[PDB]
Amino acid sequence: MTSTVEFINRWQRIALLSQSLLELAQRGEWDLLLQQEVSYLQSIETVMEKQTPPGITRSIQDMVAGYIKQTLDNEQLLKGLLQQRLDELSSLIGQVLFQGPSAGLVPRGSGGIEGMTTRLTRWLTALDNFEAKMALLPAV
Image 1 (cartoon, one colour):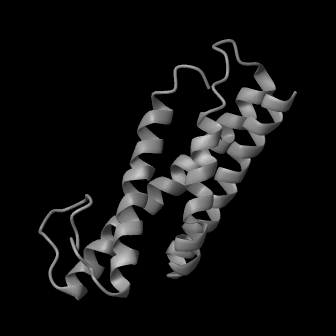
Image 2 (spheres, one colour):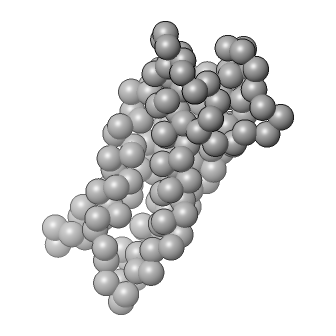
């Protein structure tokens, strides 16, 4: 049951990762967001590579759908929080737009803020990508 184990375990990892990253975002610990970033996005992509058949079984789908509720709620709260956070941060760095919930805040950071902005913008658009594409999953 290798594909079963990988599918449920990876959804479990994404659920626990997004939960952890949510708590950290609520506490202001952006450091572990930047670290576990690559971990979270990797787990997302690799579970989505495990395309399960239309006729998925009861227990698998129930546990998976639970982890899907976890990660989509955690990442929803992450998405809005980090959208408003990068909003404020770009306002601190220079000036934010009245509306700019996309990859446009700080075009050339140059110094240490360069990595922060480019990561978290690629991150938010990869979150929105996961959200959308996994909602578009015809067979999970």
